[PDB]
Amino acid sequence: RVSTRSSLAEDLRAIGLADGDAVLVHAALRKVGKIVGGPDDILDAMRDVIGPAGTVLGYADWQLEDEIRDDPAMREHIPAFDPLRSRSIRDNGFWPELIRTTPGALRSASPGASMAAIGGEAEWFTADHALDYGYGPRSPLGKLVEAKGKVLMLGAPLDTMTLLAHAEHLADFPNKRILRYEAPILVDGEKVWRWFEEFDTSDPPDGLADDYFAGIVEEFLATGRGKRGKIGEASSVLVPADEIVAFAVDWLERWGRTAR
Amino acid sequence: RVSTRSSLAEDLRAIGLADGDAVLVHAALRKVGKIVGGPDDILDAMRDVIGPAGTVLGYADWQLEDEIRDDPAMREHIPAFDPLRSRSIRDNGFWPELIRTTPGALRSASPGASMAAIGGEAEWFTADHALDYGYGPRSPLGKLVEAKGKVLMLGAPLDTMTLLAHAEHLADFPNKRILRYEAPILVDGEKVWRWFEEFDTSDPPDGLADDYFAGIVEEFLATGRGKRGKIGEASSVLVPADEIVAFAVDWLERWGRTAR
Ligand SMILES: CC(=O)SCCNC(=O)CCNC(=O)[C@H](O)C(C)(C)COP(=O)(O)OP(=O)(O)OC[C@H]1O[C@@H](n2cnc3c(N)ncnc32)[C@H](O)[C@@H]1OP(=O)(O)O
Ligand SMILES: CC(=O)SCCNC(=O)CCNC(=O)[C@H](O)C(C)(C)COP(=O)(O)OP(=O)(O)OC[C@H]1O[C@@H](n2cnc3c(N)ncnc32)[C@H](O)[C@@H]1OP(=O)(O)O
Ligand SMILES: [Cl-]
């Protein structure tokens, strides 16, 4: 079975992508199977479906390891985060690099939370991304909710849905672990070390498993409010951003009130 | 032992890179070893050594496979070669992709022979790349010789020195295999299939081994006119482009006169 730009576009329309949509995609590209024009056919087909005014996103992050950021002897040899040159974290697969290196793509400024975006509103989604609490309202994720966008899990494991970290941020529950770290960025065109602060997106709230995002998504799909479908050979899920965030905040806040 | 932008720069100086140099690099990056800022440190270090007027090149090619290209049923789903969008052939390693996706880089128009270039003369090296016989004088390889540039095998096996296919083009020896194939390119901004003609660069001249480039390089190094040295943990070779081509034309033409 071989996918084409044409056939991938019909698979994306079948799962629910439509004209003007903004969609953040998480992908395990190897699950799509054989593609005539390679994985670029997927991005091209998406843009065919949503049109030039739509926007595709991918979770770029960057490749600074904590083993490295923290080892002080290597401190001066670590390049600053540069949203135009820092490659995406390889843990998130080729897909965000695919977007980031496509002509016309943009990438936001908050390093660990940084998002790549292409399409009509890429300038809007990537701009004014808060350095601290980069998963809150002033981020591509918060604008995805405001713009009533969607999340596509393209063969990706369901617990890699980064949008639910934005739910973690909004949700009121006790003893949110705050994380503080120091990373090099650009200030006035020069490398500067800056202290960051965010809610922890690396580990779950104490008392839930590392993969509980997957459970939340499966509960949301159980309500019938999402859509499952095949993109190429990859089993995929399309959910509305605003609904799943409200769903996830609800879940987290109720779980929080079960404390003593 | 970990490499840095600084330490790779000193390694590149030790092997013979100098201000203003134009260097086409073939790389097996995995055996550079650990690099603090990843393989982009190598390119940054090269640019530190050669300066903004120097030029780094990598051999991009592109990804259209003969299986697909030849298959008539998928001919219409095969995207045209776009020097701005078509990713590098993956069996040349990450290095040409690394250059091609670096801001400011350029890429030439002859698909199978196409070269990515960044630096002071990148416009000149990538301009006017002949579609037929893309390894002859009107190519980045011909301009490398004219500019008296260099080739650096950065941990790469010596028989991957594509510059020697330019020597194959020049060398007068009998019964050169001519290759004819068709491939989709951009004409007037739209996809058009075009027939191509070149000397064979995928198979050696009848009567030589698939890796005879390696033997030529090793015998050139035995004249004393190349330099060996380690870039990071990778065994590397630096040769002048003009001399090795003249050396290889000599070798091929003498081998050709042993017929009859
Ligand atoms: C809680 C959080 O926030 S987690 C953060 C977000 N994480 C994510 O979004 C990740 C979602 N994906 C996953 O979790 C997947 O399981 C991941 C990526 C580990 C693994 O996915 P897999 O498909 O192995 O890998 P990936 O998605 O990179 O696809 C690889 C396909 O690349 C194509 N590809 C990669 N690079 C290129 C290229 N340069 N040119 C052409 N094709 C390429 C290939 O077909 C490659 O596979 P191959 O190695 O067989 O050739
Ligand atoms: C006849 C002809 O004309 S032949 C044509 C020319 N051919 C060439 O120039 C190829 C020369 N190289 C070779 O032959 C080598 O043996 C090749 C590439 C097969 C194999 O090289 P190897 O190092 O495996 O592979 P490569 O050079 O791609 O280095 C790989 C890695 O680089 C860095 N890497 C790759 N992608 C990224 C990325 N996205 N971000 C950061 N680093 C990356 C990594 O460390 C990745 O390795 P890992 O998988 O261990 O993490
Ligand atoms: Cl309740």
Image (cartoon, coloured by chain):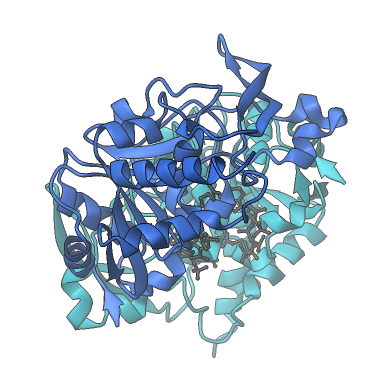
Chain colours: A cyan, B blue
Q: Position of residue A2 (x, y in %)?
A: 83, 43
**In this view of the protein, which residue sits in the foreground, B85 or B90?**
B90
Res. B101 visible in picture: no
Q: Classify B14 as above or below A180.
A: above
User: In which quadrant is the C terminus of chain B drawn?
Assistant: top right
**In this view of the protein, which residue sits in the foreground, A256 or A84?**
A84
Horizontal side of residue B120 vs A138, given as left or right: left
- Which residue sits at x=16%, y=41%? B52
Ligand 3 placement by image quarter: bottom right
Q: Classify B91 as above or below B167.
A: below
Q: Position of residue B20 (x, y in %)?
A: 15, 42
Horizontal side of residue A152 vs B220, given as left or right: right
Q: Position of residue B178 (x, y in %)?
A: 65, 29
- Which residue sits at x=82%, y=31%? B74
- Which residue sits at x=64%, y=59%? A247
- Quadrant in which residue B167 is drawn: top left
- Which residue sits at x=68%, y=69%? A214
Res. B65 visible in picture: yes
Q: Classify A205 as above or below A242.
A: below
Q: Position of residue A12 (x, y in %)?
A: 75, 38
Horizontal side of residue B43 vs A251, given as left or right: left
Residue lying furthest top: B188
Residue lying furthest bottom: A260
**In this view of the protein, which residue sits in the foreground, A123 or B36?**
B36
- Quadrant in which residue A251 is drawn: bottom right
